[PDB]
Image (tube, rainbow, N blue to C red; front, side):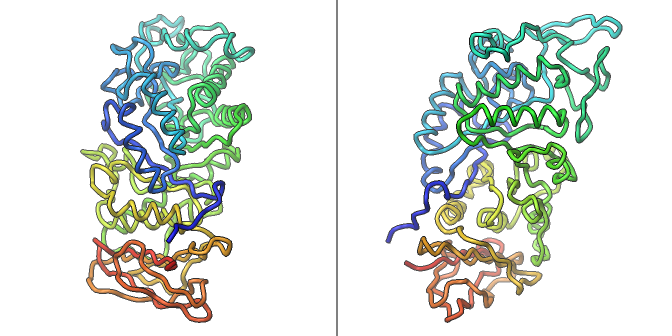
Length: 462
C-alpha cells in the first residue's frame, strides 16, 4: 500500500549533520551521492561543515576561519580548495541538494578570525596579528554587488575588539550573553562597517551561493544586538523563510533566546542531552525529560543526541558521553511533535546506525503527525508517547515506546492511541505481530526491554 501523503508544506523538517570532527575531506564531490538515499528516507535539510577558508588550509575542519568570502575559490592559507573542495564543487553539491529537495545550512563562524597575514603595530598597544588581506572579500564585497551595504575599509586591527583577553585601543567587547573573548582576533560587531559587510555576506550566502539557512557557531560569545539585526536583515532580504539555529552552549538557553529577541532564531537543545547521558547508563528514570523541547520555547528547539564536540575521539571537552541506548534517544527526538531533530553523521555512518536509524527517519517523515500526547503510565524503566495522526491523512499517527533497561523480554502498556478500532504494527520490526485498539482507542502495546532493540514505533496497518 502507499505511504501517507503529507501535504508538502506540512512535511516534518529532519536535519542531518553531514560531518563530524576531521571527517570527509573532499566532501563536496561526494555529497550528492551521500544525500540521495538520505532524501529518500526523509532527510529534508543538511548542516554542512563550515565552508569558508580556514587558517590551516585543507587540514582545517573550518572553525579557525580566515576569509568568509573564500569558499574554496582563492589561493589563501596554502590552498585554493578548502578541506571539502573548491567553490565550484560546492556549487555543484548545492544544485544536487536542491534537486533532491534538501536545504543546505551554512556553518558560520562570526566570533573571531584566525590566520592574519601580517603583524601590525597598534598605536598605544603594541604588536598584534591583525592584518587580513581577504582575497574573497576583494572579489565579492563590492558596490557593484551590494550598493549601500558596501564600505571601503581594510580588515586591520580596527576591525577587531582585541585578542588574548585584551581590548585594542578604543574598543569594547560588545553586549555578549556569555563571556566575549574565546580565541583568535575577536571581531568588532559594534563597528558599523563590519555590521554592514556581514549583512551583504548573508545575502550572498543565501541569494547568490544558494544556501537555505545558517548554523551560528559560538554565537553566545557574539554581540547580541548585532546577532538580532543581522538575522532580521537576512530574513527580510530573502524570498524564502531562512533557517537560523544558534550554537548557544550556555546554561540558560531560553534566556539567550529571550535576549536576542528575534522570532527567526532557533537554538540547539544542549540541556536535553543530559537525559541521553542518563539513558546511556541503563538507569535513567524514564518518567521525565528536560530540555528546551520540553519548555515554552519548544518550537525553537533543534534537538540532537551528539555532535562533533560532544562525541569526538579523545573527548577533548571532557563531556559525559552518550554510548548506549542511542536508537532510543533518536526515537525520542525524531517523533516529538515539536523541535527539529538532527541526525549526526558520526552515529549514522562511523558507528553504523543507518540500518535502524533509517526506519526512525522514515517514521518521522511519514507517521509523526498530529498532536502529541504524553503518557500517564510511564515507569522508571519505560517511556511512551503518542502522535494522534491527522484525520485527513489516514495511516498517520504512532505509539512510541522506549526501554531504558536491558532486562530482556517484553513489557506492555495500555495506551490511548486516539485511533479507535484500529490495527497497529511495529514499523521498526522490533516487536512482531499486531495490536488492536478498542472503541475508545486503547490498546496494549509491547516494547522489548533491551538496550539493543528496546524501541517500538506502532503505526496503523494499511
